[PDB]
Length: 195
Length: 130
Image 1 (cartoon, chains in turn green, blue):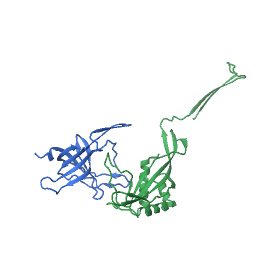
Image 2 (tube, rainbow over the protein chains, first blue to last red):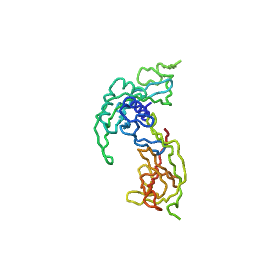
Image 3 (spheres, rainbow over the protein chains, first blue to last red):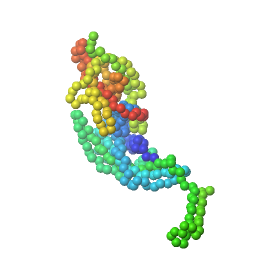
Image 4 (cartoon, rainbow over the protein chains, first blue to last red):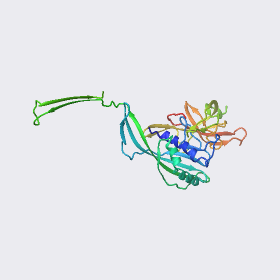
């Protein structure tokens, strides 16, 4: 199954291991990779972490690959498999954000990294966008940000608990000489079971 | 009979200032929150855009928001990203409030030094833990 929340969680763990040697460390010496719009229970907001930090944000989830990729039957349930394409926005904030972002791009193509990302997420990278060197004016100085749009593709399998598959077929057939003949010339009754 | 201590409310302060980001990536607020009664004056904030007790007719329902000013001598804090502070929650009629924006007249005069706070009602939201 596909859950955007789980996908963002999976990406964050990957970014910590992949690009962690260039970010800042908190009180637990954990590289500052956070999910966008942080918030705990109810309205408990989240503080802006230290500089060189990474923000992960799943922009949306489109399905340009058709309504249903395939429909198979599991043990006793009909399972639909839909193909999704999730654009995830990874943005690095802080001084020298562009240099940090560039390293991640050249590191998101390595086979070892993508194999790691394929695990614990279940998705595979489709492509990586362009990195704009953005300068925004907060209050006094300019904060460097380098957003990047990583596009992921994943297959979600959901089970319809109201399937009730076929196991027996009963066929009644008649043979006639012309279109009509209310008394059929010969009658066919079939009964095929899975036993 | 100081007007500065007319009303009495209960403030929840995140005393155990931990506020760390879990390994997964979400935000884990302070696990220890204490509620101790304070005293202050709560008045409606009348300034232009700021709306007090105003129902907002959205195409999804009717939401209600308000903004009150708070004169008090207590040092209530606000969410700060340098000292890892996590704001203070004021309570009026049960509904939780948040201390956005602060004015610090703490040392200026002798018998009139006070803090001025801008308390905002917290919007209704589904709660999920992390």
